Image (cartoon, coloured by chain):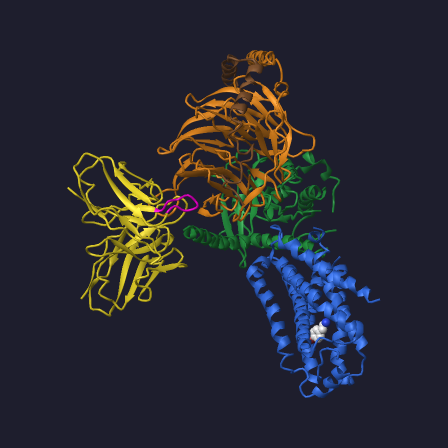
Chain colours: A yellow, B green, C orange, D brown, E blue
Amino acid sequence: VQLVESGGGLVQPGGSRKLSCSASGFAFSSFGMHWVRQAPEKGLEWVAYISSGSGTIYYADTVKGRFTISRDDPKNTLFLQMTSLRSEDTAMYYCVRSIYYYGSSPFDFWGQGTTLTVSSADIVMTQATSSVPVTPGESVSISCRSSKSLLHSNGNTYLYWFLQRPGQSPQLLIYRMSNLASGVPDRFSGSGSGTAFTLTISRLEAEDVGVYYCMQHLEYPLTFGAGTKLEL
Amino acid sequence: EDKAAVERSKMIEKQLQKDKQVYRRTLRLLLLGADNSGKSTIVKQMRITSGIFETKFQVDKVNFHMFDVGAQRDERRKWIQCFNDVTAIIFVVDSNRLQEALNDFKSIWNNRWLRTISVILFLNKQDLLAEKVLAKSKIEDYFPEFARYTTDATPEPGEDPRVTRAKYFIRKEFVDISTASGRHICYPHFTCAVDTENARRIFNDCKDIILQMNLREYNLV
Amino acid sequence: ELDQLRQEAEQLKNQIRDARKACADATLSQITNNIDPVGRIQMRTRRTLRGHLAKIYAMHWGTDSRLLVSASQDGKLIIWDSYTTNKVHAIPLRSSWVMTCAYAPSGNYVACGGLDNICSIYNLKTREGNVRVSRELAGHTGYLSCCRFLDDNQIVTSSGDTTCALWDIETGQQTTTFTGHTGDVMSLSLAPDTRLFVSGACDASAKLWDVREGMCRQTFTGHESDINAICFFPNGNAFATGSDDATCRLFDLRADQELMTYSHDNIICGITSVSFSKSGRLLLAGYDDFNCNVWDALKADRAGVLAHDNRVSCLGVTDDGMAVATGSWDSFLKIWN
Amino acid sequence: SIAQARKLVEQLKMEANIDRIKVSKAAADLMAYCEAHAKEDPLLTPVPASENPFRE
Amino acid sequence: LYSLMSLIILATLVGNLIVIISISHFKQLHTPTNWLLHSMAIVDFLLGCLIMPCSMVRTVERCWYFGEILCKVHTSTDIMLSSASIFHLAFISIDRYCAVCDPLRYKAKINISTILVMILVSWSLPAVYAFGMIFLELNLKGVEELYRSQVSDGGCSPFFSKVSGVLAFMTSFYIPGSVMLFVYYRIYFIAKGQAKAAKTLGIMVGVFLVCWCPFFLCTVLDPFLGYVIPPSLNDALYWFGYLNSALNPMVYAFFYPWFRR
Ligand SMILES: NCCc1ccc(Br)cc1
């Protein structure tokens, strides 16, 4: 399981570029795929989406007529084509895996990223703070606030935590506000009530430093949080 | 958003449709040779502790499917239920290693799960009988009514009446068992280990079987 | 000299039967006279699971109480979602004549074995997006007739060569072999404490085995024809069978006798599957005349009928007692509630 | 066959010595378990159509 | 008197309803040929429920007091549904020939894809042919004077010229009849050779020929004869043609075991 992205560079405004994420090591024909953007000094932001059978495509409201997404199953390659580059499309781009069936864990594996430089009714997610000083060996807590009830009629509560380590790609820690990922150490937990959410870490080591993100998945516009860095 | 789950289900169903088409266009066959009956020769059909030995062969753009049977001990009472839907049964017998063959034939006839399945019976190694007659075949010893037996028919030229008498004696010994029952019919053939027309015989027999089935369907008979 | 030994053996068999018979103070039926009957039970079909090309042979609920798996003559394993009718997985097999399936207690594996003498293990949760076979257990001679999971490691198999077995998946090697049956063994069931398991064979007898010591413990007889299905009481002290002679019986475990029989004079066809309710109050059996009947486990009264276009081949009751699933030879699964 | 017979006779002896109880007591714990868990049986007593996930 | 015909109308309504739902909802009968039977039943049901009451009011008292606007619509719909019925009969015959004559490749050559194509073609082409033949007045072009006198004399009937009538007759009776008659001959010979065949085939052929020859024969002959025949025989032949819709579910879906079911 590994995804390697190609493309990027410095582009004058008004041009067009074609980014690629090459998949090798799993079944590329059974996974949905996204693209997620990261401004250099800001949190993440959603870009696009294309499902397994190429039957459903969504776009972020920011750019809808300028970007297009497509996939090529036989060669295991994912494409993004963009046109009329403004000064805002100057950020990092990540290709993210996702598989949807009862009991699965979406957004589990993230790519490595590529760099690029250019010379309303959606749910608002906010985090209480942006930093916190602590000491190794004791518990910490991080709070997330929502502008609408994320709890659905079926009973699920769609909330995710990612915890991007300082220097590499983001990971997955908790999906749907209570459930734990596969390879994460068993000292993370999550709880919530419907509008307010908290993340607790029991112990603390040298690997826990980084920035924690708060994502929602109730409706297509995906609003990411701001991030609370842990400084040691 | 369970819409992605619904999309996954729909793609699975789309593949199942293609599988159904391929399944519906094919024909299955069961082989029930005896112990010493040389079905190993009749399965030489490449020129067109395991169990089921699946093979495939096609003639004139029609796909067949022959299932041999492996190490399933000795009793066939329970695993014969799975073959309630095949197109035909293909015996192989050797021409006293005949009485047990007759008993096995009549046991496989008049079952409760093989009531509507026709039998394509094969007579393998038709040189043993000829050599025994020419030289050792004391049929009257264990078949007393051989002496008081005779045919009109359409024999094959270049043979004495004795060999033909023996051949249709055995053939009648099978046909009477078949007729002592009309939902299905037996198809006796005299063949040899190294032959050429075996696939052709199976083709014509299956064609006749399903033709009778279709005529029954629209009450043309 | 063989007769000498034979005589002594029959001598023992004489002592066992008389000692067992000189224990019945009163029947199971008499002891339940006081109680009010369940009455009439009406069950309405809620879902209808479609997609199988051909006739269905087995199914097994998951511990999650929501998922189930089923197998068919096509050579397909499909995992359903009983709430929203979706399909989660569709697994194609190497051999098309499959008779069994089981769903792991933790929800990680599914296994199936058929008429080709091999039990296969599939890994559902993997770093890829596909289901792969991880072990192929070989060593039986006849066809496999049942299989049940103990852990993510230990499995129990029943075959058509009159033997049961206990395996070790990572090594792939047979650990214990249970011998003693005369005819080919048709089904087995486990126990709540996972220390004992029962088995029923075509020699018209059922035996109770111990997993650790690998030896037989008891033997129950009374059935005229072969045994098709066996199930275990929730308490752990009883079990019920279903045979080809249109009879279902109930046997005590530590009393070593035969309790009430469940039969009627309007049925001539045999039984294919039996299963219990959560409280043990109802015994429901799948029949051969296209119908499934539900019985009162304590007084033998027909109370309800679950009316399929062909023979019913499998049953199941969820761990927490929501619903009942049935399969048949015309290829549709129905969930009754 | 004597070797086979020896195994067979050995079995019967082992199965002969098993402790047994009265049928009346063995037929009472069944009813006790039926009664002490009759309330937890959604299949016996139908559950109101609000916590039934198989509605419609 | 007038009431005797009603029974027909009930028949066209009952016969079709029972086929429609005996196959509408049954998981055992979703076979590809049963869809052709289903479509035929729908066509006959629509023909009955719509056309017959207007024929009632027209033939009881010999006038059409519903306006010149709806006359064209009614005739167009009638041609639609009659042509659809005959086309479905021809397609059922082709399907039955594909079964018996070559049995090994039956299920390959007749699947759920081709039958949908035949259903859509047999529904569509009569629609285009009908109105395209009515609203644009190609049927009576050049002879409009005669229909003016006849309507002034108010009945609404399909008026055909010398070429219009022949085209309707050869683009509707003859091609379907030709493909039905050729195919229930070879089947009879093959059944007789390889195995009652006549007692089942002759019935179908005779019912279809009795129902549909007189009407189309008189229709094609009338322009040559000079429009001399009285409208009473025309109405009798309309009733004879309507009888075919009632008789269809009997011959194709009730002489069989599934017909017992
Ligand atoms: N009731 C049938 C009336 C009719 C007349 C002409 C054509 Br061409 C077809 C149908």
Find residue A9 and report its horizontal and vertical position in percent.
20, 63
Is B151 or A93 nearer to us in this picture?
A: A93
Is B20 or A141 nearer to us in this picture?
A: A141
The magenta stretch spans residue A154: yes
Image quadrant for the N terminus of chain C? Answer: top right
Is residue A62 among what the camera can see? yes
A58 sits left or right of B156 in the view:
left
E68 sits left or right of A227 in the view:
right
Give the vertical position of E177 relative to A37 (above or below): below
Residue drawn at x 62%, y 47% as measured from the top left: B120
Find residue E28 and report its horizontal and vertical position in percent.
62, 50
- Residue projecting furthest to the right: E1
Which SS type dominates the magenta stretch? Answer: loop
Residue drawn at x 30%, y 64% as measured from the top left: A81
Find residue C156 and report its horizontal and vertical position in percent.
44, 30
Find residue C150 and report its horizontal and vertical position in percent.
42, 30
Q: What stretch is highlighted in magenta?
A: A150-158
Image quadrant for the C terminus of chain C? Answer: top right
Residue drawn at x 75%, y 80% as measured from the top left: E154
Is residue C140 among what the camera can see? no
Q: In which quarter of the image is residue C173?
A: top left
Give the vertical position of D27 relative to B24 (above or below): above
The magenta stretch spans residue E198: no
Is A190 or B141 nearer to us in this picture?
A: A190
Give the vertical position of A192 relative to C281 (above or below): below
C220 sits left or right of E147 in the view:
left
Q: Quadrant of residue B32?
A: top right
